[PDB]
Image (cartoon, rainbow over all chains, first blue to last red; front, side, top):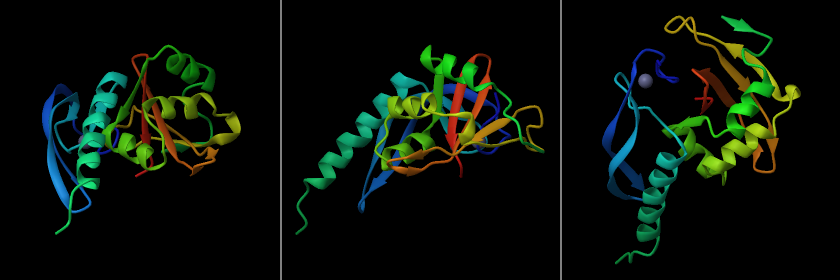
Length: 70
Length: 97
Ligand SMILES: [Zn+2]
């Protein structure tokens, strides 16, 4: 299928490390599985993939929200 | 490049979702999270749709064979624009850009 956002890139199954920023902090979310647009940065994910992504996102936000500001 | 009728019958949309035959874009997932909705949350919104929530179906020059059905349900969390495409018996859900 073609990407639902850019409408050009074919979507290809794969793994990527995805940068993520939250409240002035950042991480790279490792080994995110999905269908990745070859043209833009969009991806498509099923339930399992979505839940695992959001768990890493939510783990990182938990870490940042507890972090001391000096 | 727009129609006033949905490309996929809403009964078929719900059948796919009720069979777990659903995927979402990463942007839609993060967007839904801001509204307090997880993946299952998005599925519940889709199964709560009526025909009256339908806005329009649209295609593009880049992908002229593919249609996206746009719905705008009013939720406790606010009014949300969902875009749905059915590709080989899998529902693909995104949010208006
Ligand atoms: Zn794309």
